[PDB]
Image 1 (cartoon, rainbow over the protein chains, first blue to last red):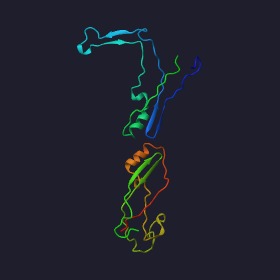
Image 2 (image 1 turned 30 degrees about the vertical axis):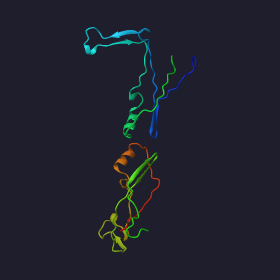
Image 3 (image 1 turned 90 degrees about the vertical axis):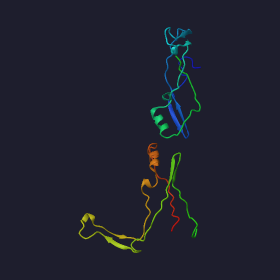
Image 4 (image 1 turned 90 degrees about the horizontal axis):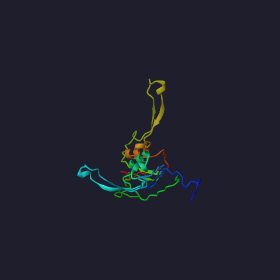
Length: 102
Length: 102
């Protein structure tokens, strides 16, 4: 889309309060290494662990983007503005973007 | 207008916040006596007073309605809502009513 030398996005970190809505936007810089050396590895609890700690699963070479915390979208001033003036809130919709990939 | 037995007004004490406006309404019950026994009396500073305290004026049999204080229109919760969220405020217009006169 933008080959080499053309930016594919802009930095949008801000919040807009409009009546009964607040739209919070956040931008961060991420680093993604190579996980498991491009391999899927079966993982399980160590031998000798207690029965409560036993588990079985798989480790993937993929990563994931997590923003399931309020601090990822609300500044402390935004939080104070939200909690001192509103009797409730709920999420409505979200937009996600990855850009400027090197 | 309402002769004897018909109310000439209602009790409106409340505040409405609408965007960049807040309208505060207050109703009070007042008592007005007879002042100076229906007379205008010349008044002046007492003899022997200091020069800084000397004055001359007149006392009238009339009363006056004063609402030149913020507590006359804003409840403490209204004041907290005003001062914790706004960088400024100013009055725009007012409406005054006397009713249910006995």
